[PDB]
Image 1 (cartoon, helix red, strand yellow):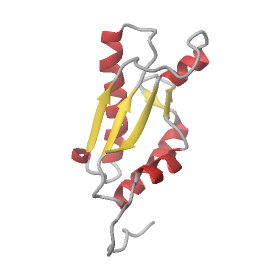
Image 2 (cartoon, helix red, strand yellow):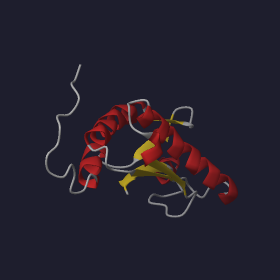
Image 3 (cartoon, one colour):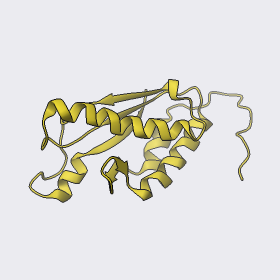
Image 4 (spheres, helix red, strand yellow):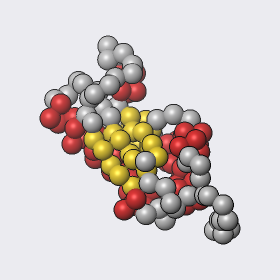
Length: 131
């Protein structure tokens, strides 16, 4: 396997966000059972957790998003849950879940056409930003 990161000397990260967005290449898409992320996302997420381990002084915010198709009062708890799924998975990689924040915004800002299930699938995403 891989060995734990060597001891730092200077600052660990100037801005871990640049490492996270580079690894993710985008937001986290969901699908399959719906309450699960895409199989390819886990692969990317494992790579994200790696960076978190490489930067234990960093806190991450996992904000969940969904489309405005369902009820907003229902969308919010959902978005938060999907966000938690990601947070949980990171913990399983050794990442401190206490330094991981989960936010559910429901349907606040769509990015794709709701007229299509395809675009709707983009409106429902999870994003990881460094706090």
